[PDB]
Image (cartoon, rainbow, N blue to C red; front, side, top):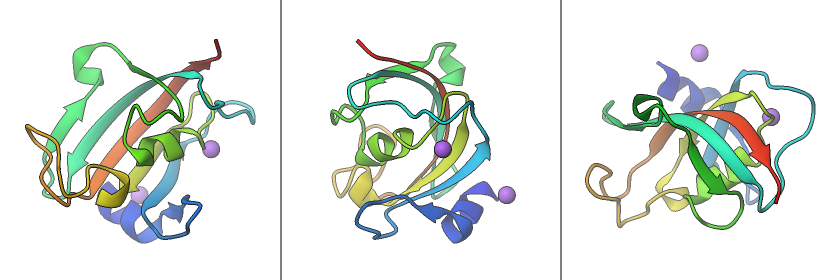
Length: 128
Ligand code: NA
Ligand code: NA
């Protein structure tokens, strides 16, 4: 399925080239521009654990998730991955725990040492 495919066929987008964040572009976005550090980014996403369980979805809340890019307001894999996206792009990210929640995990649903799969849509980005 999609998590296996990004694991085996994804692109390493880390600057360390340690395979910690792998990406596949699923829907090509608009133009060439990617968001800049500090931009307000608006995303829709779904996240799955490596046991197949959905742990989160913004679609199910009928509102996007909004954060300031590159500020550590989200897991490292998202700061790195969203920074590569064009407006309107949909991608898959496969995130090793060192770029996610590490040994701590995140209650209620994310265990220790968890590799995470996300589908992410970059809806918009805006500077301030
Ligand atoms: Na595929
Ligand atoms: Na891209």
